[PDB]
Amino acid sequence: IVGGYTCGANTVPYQVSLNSGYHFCGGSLINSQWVVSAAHCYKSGIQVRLGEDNINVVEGNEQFISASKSIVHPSYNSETYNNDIMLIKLKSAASLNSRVASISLPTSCASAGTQCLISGWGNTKSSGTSYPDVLKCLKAPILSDSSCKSASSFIITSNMFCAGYLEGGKDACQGDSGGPVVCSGKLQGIVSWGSGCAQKNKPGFYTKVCNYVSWIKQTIASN
Ligand SMILES: N=C(N)c1cccc(-c2nocc2C(=O)Nc2ccc(-c3ccccc3S(N)(=O)=O)cc2)c1
Ligand SMILES: [Ca+2]
């Protein structure tokens, strides 16, 4: 997160860190046994870290749980970044509490102008590199489909939305990938991609979760 604020410990209790010896992506807890993340985050040997604020220090509310299965969406295409969503099942059920909680799936898609909460432990600078230890937060509005398209030298599919600030300065970044975009108490977005971070006319793009609820629900039922 570039140009955001310190969330405060456990204020985003569905925020999850994916660890393979180091933090590499965010995720969202959607029930006691399932995490939703980004397809482009896939890798073997993932450990899901719940209840984190400072990811470098044992603070007392962590739950670390191994992934038992990962399911990348059938149609995830890394040349297009289309369908950038993956489900991770945990080897044991998380103990749910005030600091470790699930986030509701959307029943309907969010609209342009809607203010959303985006969070992660990703890079905090548009130029250079600084990675925070505690969780950062950014409130950003969803931007129109037309301005999203105009502000991108890549192809934008209907399973993407963009959000943030065309002026620049405020955006998610590398390391935030996979993490939540929460709008009116529903998981609407997954940090998917951006051309650099927080640059002029280079807004953040996110996986349109509302499009996937049926697949999410059916896959969980069956695994
Ligand atoms: N600024 C952001 N919102 C953001 C969020 C997460 C990661 C990064 C990021 N931090 O550094 C680089 C990054 C990046 O995402 N680069 C990037 C650019 C384009 C694509 C892409 C988009 C559509 C089709 C194809 C591609 S791709 N993968 O072929 O290039 C993928 C990744 C930035
Ligand atoms: Ca910690």
Image (tube, grey):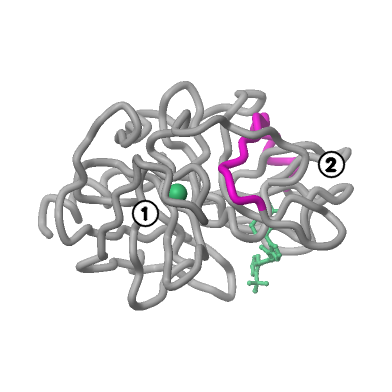
Residue 49, numbered circle: 1
Image quarter (top left, top right, bottom left or bottom right) of the C terminus: bottom left
Residue type indicated by callout 1: Arg
In the image, which residues are magenta?
132-148
Residue at the image point whose x is 57% and y is 27% from the top: 111
User: Which of the two discs, 1 and 2, sits closer to the camera?
Assistant: 1
Between the residue at mark 1 and the residue at mark 2, the CA separation in whole angstroms equals 29 Å
Whether residue 36 is situated above or below residue 119 in the rendered picture: below
Q: Quadrant of residue 13?
A: top left
Mark 2 Cα-neighbour bin, 10 Å: few <14, some 14–19, many ≥20:
some
CB of mark 2 near ligand 1 (< 8 Å): no
Horizontal side of residue 10 vs 117, given as left or right: left
Give the image quadrant in which the ligand numbered 1 is located: bottom right
What's the residue at 37%, 61% (across, down)? 86
Q: Which mark is residue 210?
A: none
Residue 82, how many percent across, how many down?
52, 63
> Label 2: which residue?
169
Is label 1 in a helix, a strand or a loop? strand
Residue 96 position in % (x across, y down): 22, 35
Residue 140 covered by magenta stretch = yes
The verdict on label 1 being within 8 Å of ligand 2 is yes
Horizontal arrangement in the rendering, residue 7 relative to residue 35 (left or right)? right
Using the image as rendered, state which of residue 76 and residue 124 is in the foreground. Answer: 124
Task: Residue 177: name its quadrant.
Answer: bottom right
Residue under the image location 41 percent in, 29 percent down: 186
Outermost residue on the left side: it is 222
